[PDB]
Image (cartoon, coloured by chain):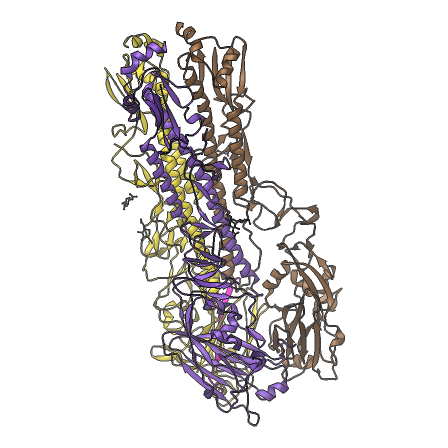
Chain colours: A purple, B yellow, C brown
Amino acid sequence: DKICIGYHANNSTTQVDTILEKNVTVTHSVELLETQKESRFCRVLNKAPLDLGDCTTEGWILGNPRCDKLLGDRSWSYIVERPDAQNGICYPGVLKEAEELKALIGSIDTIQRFEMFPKSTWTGVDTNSGVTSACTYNGGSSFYRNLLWIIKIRSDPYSLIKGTYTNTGSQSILYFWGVHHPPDDVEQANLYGLGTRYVRMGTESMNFAKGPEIADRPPANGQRGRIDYYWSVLKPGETLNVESNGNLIAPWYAYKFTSSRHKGAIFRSDLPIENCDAVCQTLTGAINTNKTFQNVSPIWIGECPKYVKSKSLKLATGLRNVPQIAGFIEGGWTGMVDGWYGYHHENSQGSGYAADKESTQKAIDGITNKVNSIIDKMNTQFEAVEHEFSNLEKRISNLNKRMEDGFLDVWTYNAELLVLLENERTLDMHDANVKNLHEKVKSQLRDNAKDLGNGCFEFWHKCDNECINSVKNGTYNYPKYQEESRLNRE
Amino acid sequence: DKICIGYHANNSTTQVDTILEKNVTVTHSVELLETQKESRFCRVLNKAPLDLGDCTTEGWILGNPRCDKLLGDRSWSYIVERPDAQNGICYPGVLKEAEELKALIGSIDTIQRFEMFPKSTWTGVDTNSGVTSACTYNGGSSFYRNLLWIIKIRSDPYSLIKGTYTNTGSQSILYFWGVHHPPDDVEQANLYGLGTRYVRMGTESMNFAKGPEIADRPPANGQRGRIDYYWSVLKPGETLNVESNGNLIAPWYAYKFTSSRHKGAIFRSDLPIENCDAVCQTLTGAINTNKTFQNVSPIWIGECPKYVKSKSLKLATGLRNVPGGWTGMVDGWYGYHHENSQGSGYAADKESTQKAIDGITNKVNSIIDKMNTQFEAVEHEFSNLEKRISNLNKRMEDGFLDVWTYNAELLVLLENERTLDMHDANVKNLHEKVKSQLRDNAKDLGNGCFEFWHKCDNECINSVKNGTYNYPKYQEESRLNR
Amino acid sequence: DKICIGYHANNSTTQVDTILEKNVTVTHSVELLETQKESRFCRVLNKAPLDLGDCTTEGWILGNPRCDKLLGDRSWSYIVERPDAQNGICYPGVLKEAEELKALIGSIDTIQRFEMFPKSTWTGVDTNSGVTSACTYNGGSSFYRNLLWIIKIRSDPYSLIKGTYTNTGSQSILYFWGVHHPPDDVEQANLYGLGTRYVRMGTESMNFAKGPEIADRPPANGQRGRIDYYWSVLKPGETLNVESNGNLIAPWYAYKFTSSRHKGAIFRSDLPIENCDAVCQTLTGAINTNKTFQNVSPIWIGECPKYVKSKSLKLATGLRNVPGGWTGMVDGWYGYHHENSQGSGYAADKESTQKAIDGITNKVNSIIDKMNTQFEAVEHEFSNLEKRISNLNKRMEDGFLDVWTYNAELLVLLENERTLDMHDANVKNLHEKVKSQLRDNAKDLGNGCFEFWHKCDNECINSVKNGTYNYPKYQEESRLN
Ligand SMILES: *[C@@H]1O[C@H](CO)[C@@H](O[C@@H]2O[C@H](CO)[C@@H](O)[C@H](O)[C@H]2NC(C)=O)[C@H](O)[C@H]1NC(C)=O
Ligand SMILES: *[C@@H]1O[C@H](CO)[C@@H](O)[C@H](O)[C@H]1NC(C)=O
Ligand SMILES: *[C@@H]1O[C@H](CO)[C@@H](O)[C@H](O)[C@H]1NC(C)=O
Ligand SMILES: *[C@@H]1O[C@H](CO)[C@@H](O)[C@H](O)[C@H]1NC(C)=O
Ligand SMILES: *[C@@H]1O[C@H](CO)[C@@H](O)[C@H](O)[C@H]1NC(C)=O
């Protein structure tokens, strides 16, 4: 006649690691790391990304005429720029503060294009010949649709020209202009005239006065001339004045815009945009998951889990899985099934397995709480950003990089280390819970049963089902069987 | 006759959390997080902050004439700017590198104002008409007290003008100038003259050369003109040369300054400045605490505890409070209750109580020790063309805050669970030390107590406590009773 | 007749700390922190650093004529600038974007100097009088070897001058120029001429047009004039055009360069450069170690361990050393001491000793594995107008340092306590395996040993060790006693 203390086992082959031991098979586990993504770009909070097609952010916003598919009012949750986009700044030159412009654009929600300065604002000049082979449209010469390249009428001098616009709305306005620099004085004379020339732009809060910076330079996109492109934001209430007597690339169309209530982004990617929705949209695809870590990409919008370098974060929730009557010391019981820890008895009324409800449940609750506590404490994300840096910003670019890789290494370490350490605790907690049941039984039976050093106890007497249950509920009664016992123990 | 092993309990209702379970009542705990502050600004290392009143940092340092209350020599542990301050850059324009100037000013300790270039320096020009309705003083037109707005005499051309100053002291000098930009060529001709005009400033180590950038603009503060304001530091030994034939807003008064040996700050706040002292002064008030974390503010000067987002960090120092436990023990944490013919009573086990007290006190102090650093967020400012480094700074500051908060919260949960396991084990040890000694001269009861099969006097009971029991002496008397 | 359960001890005096107690002596420990360095500069991936001697990075790269020891093709894994170097920008003025130039230079691995614009490119001007007392060479007046200071011939006007160069290679080219600003109109007229003057430089991707900004300024290095120095990179394929009628300090020699596949650095240090190799080279010396943390310096190139502020990170790998414990055990960590009529002796329990050795070894390696990453501080420079990003960089670097230090110190304290608890438990297990087997055929003694109520031969004692004891066989003989 006997009773054993033992623990659950099953067919699982899932392994976890601990600080002490690797490749340890367990009965139950939860993987905390999401590794799967849909390789595409989806809507976020029901708002679609803007596909720039064969255009760059600059070609788009300056209105390169090969970018007409994007022309006009648009709204977007994020921007998708194709890596090999060919249509950008077609007439050669520099966009001043280009990287800050992109940051601005990435924080914008919606834009509304409108005519800020119609051609009629500039009088005594040629508003219809401002085109170049560098900016083609259907093979012929053309120009940015948001800028107007004014030149003199052949017969007349380039008169002083003036224009004003007042932002009377509540939305800020993003607008552009340029100064054209011919490669020599002959072209300068032809297009604008000799003498001092200036482009002046004035606001309540910005002031601008510049002239041609003539110089012979090698051709870029077929052109020896250049344009310095500038951008600015006319704030609500502000008024802009424009004066020039030459070399002005005037603002034509501009954008009333709103600033997103959400984090946005410009993704440089070739992934397709499809008709789908995503809670979490990363640079390298959409994630749909309840998990709390993620090794897909550090760059995203929406609500994503923390990025880490890990290939897995398998957290043990069950016991060491070790199958082979006999109790816990020789392994686990595939036959238990009921629960995690329990008993196996054998008397004249048969035999069988039964879990200890109370200790199984107390352990389930502690583990469930542990998991939720981990989920809770990992419920923040460091958010890397794809801002851009010029060739003269190596230092802050490197600063940003070291910072982003810094937090990635700390969080990866934190996550990996936590899983290793708590797994060891989880498995020790099992060993102890089993020990507790075994010891609750041992203390009760004293010398009315033999230990066997094995997890089971052999009764020195008869133990019916009502006796065996009296051991489970912890109300055994040593004296009743003490005499019967001692006679067989001697 | 009997002896029991048990543990302490009391009237405490304080709860802590562990990784395994929540809302666990304990006998003793220490709260590690400071959440209280005095909503005011105090002295730090016995030096008072500077209240800028109705002035902004810029109005102050350029000497806006409505800011005369701040004019002259000053010194401070930190600066308090009022959010709604109205007197700043009164004549419209831009202070170049304004944000870097503020960082500088925040690292300054004391300033001494002095006349760098008196009016007599500039000859053949009008040094007495340089005033505007935009910078008013008692209703009349005026101008910044640290700058001089020079224009031509009506009859004469604006002559080339020159001035030099040499810093012969050991203190650096902070000084200001500007270039005035009229809105059109007519005003330009009136005030300075036509042709190329320049403002040139030179030093052993810096140079500067700029002209008017004339342009039609809308009025701001009633004026279509603008001034680009500039600042710089003339180092000890250096000499400054100034040369212009127009558009120069010349330096007039400047500041010899010293750099603080301590971290300083500019707080934008409406909190009152009072006659008090603070070891730790945050943007949102003063903290006086021995605690090691703090959820008041990430921005401070003085010696503050680490900022975290947590609402509490309650660390268990005692046992699970379950009255189970013995409210009657009082002596210590773990111990005994005996009963014989000489009475009964409770008594703690000194040695195991003390060993556990020392381990916990060490744990607390070890935590305090390892958390004895602070990440220090700074209130530097960023222009509208510095969105990227501004965002970089923000993500960094929040980055450390999230790692330290996680570190702190997680540590408390994990070590609380260890603390409470250690109690369970210590109690079990005493019980087992007793059991092994008595063997079958006493009955277990499965209950924590032992019923003696014999008489056990106080001398016997004490022999069990000190671990020198003597089974054979009572073995006969014992075995017969069963 | 008896058997005891006990644990190892030895002569070790090494101490570790735990979260619960301090100065705890243990039998074995591993120090995880490297504190030793060779105070010198070594080769890294077989390439030597470049010693700038008495020259600054700027004097070197502009070709200050007192820096001829460096002149020409060079290559390096890192640059060592001496703190007290005196030869830099000798004619007074400002190198634009100097700090970015240094970052560039730190990322370069080899340069090849060549004549970009020979003197013959500039016609109708004086290409042979461009010298100053501020830039001396053997006592006489001279000038940077990579720049040409052109002035007018006395009799003639300064003609418009032109030059072009096209980068037809695959390597980028680093080059320099300047604009000279005289201190007054008389010197201006003398050297270049009156009227508007300009210096124009053009490329497919950069445009430059500036004039003299004449002003009297106090003398620096004996000179009231100034030069604004500029630098740029002509990319492969690009072509540079130069046009001026005055005030041009022309490019003369420039550098084709290659970009390092590795992190480089400019170290400001007086440490000697020697014939050695270093896997890890820090600003304050070379480290050769297998350890995983390091308190030598946060600045390095090569493969270094993680920098921390700690003075030590001693991890317990053995037991509490308390000779209590058995100096006589030697075999292993946990075991037995028996005594019968066939003698006495000590013997370790192989299975439980080995399981503990493996768990600890794994713990150490796991720690090593998880700490196998480094935050890398950099010595980029910041101007006096970059206090904010300089402070941002500083707070960031000290931020990670504090987090990693905390992580490392805290981990050692916590795992040391776990390590020492695991020993206490393993010993207790052996003791309780033996107790359950013997029941009342032996006496506990409350002491760790068991006194047998019967005779226990070596075969009996081993039957206890292997866990197959046989209580009934000796139960009668026992009960008699
Ligand atoms: C995130 O981790 C997963 C695995 O946990 C990586 O995906 C595996 O990569 C291997 C080796 O290339 C493939 O053969 C397996 O098919 C992948 N496993 C799964 C489940 O997809 C993945 O590369 C990691 N992500 C990133 C961006 O590095
Ligand atoms: C713990 O107690 C608080 C009240 O202090 C209560 O709001 C909360 O719901 C409790 N949590 C759990 C898990 O019982
Ligand atoms: C922590 O401080 C916050 C400040 O954000 C305060 O409102 C709150 O009451 C604090 N939490 C607790 C539990 O004191
Ligand atoms: C142990 O602690 C004391 C101070 O409490 C210290 O003086 C002593 O040097 C320490 N020993 C070691 C080996 O660090
Ligand atoms: C590193 O720690 C060691 C002690 O292990 C000490 O001798 C040394 O001062 C430390 N080095 C530095 C640079 O702080």
Residue B170 shown in magenta: yes
Find the residue positioned furthest to the top: C480
Work out whether B176 lies above or below C403: below
Residue ranking furthest to the bottom: A155
In this rendering, would B94 be left or right of A393?
A: left
**Image quarter hosting the N terminus of chain A:** top left
Q: Quadrant of residue A129?
A: bottom right
Image quadrant occupied by the C terminus of chain A: top left
Residue positioned 44% across, 61% down in the render: A42
Vertical arrangement, residue B455 with respect to residue C397, above or below: above
| Numbered disc total | 0
Q: Is residue B68 left or right of residue C185?
A: left
Residue B390 in the image, given as x and y percentages of width and height? 46, 62
User: x and y percent of residue B27 in the render?
Assistant: 30, 35
Where on the image, by quarter, is ligand 5? Answer: top right
Residue numbers of the magenta segment: B169-185
The residue lying toward the viewer, choosing from C390 and A22, is A22
Q: How far from the left and from the top, in percent, is residue B190?
A: 48, 88
**Residue A179 drawn in magenta:** no
Instruction: Please tell me which residue lies in front, B239 or A341.
Output: A341
Residue B48 location, quadrant:
bottom left
Q: Is residue C417 left or right of residue C179?
A: left
**Residue A332 or residue B10, whichever sits in front:** A332
Q: Position of residue A480 (x, y in %)?
A: 27, 15
Q: Would you say residue A434 is visible in this rendering? A: yes
Which residue corresponds to the image point at 60% horizontal and 76% vertical from the top-left?
Answer: C216
Asked if residue C402 can be seen in this view, the reply is no
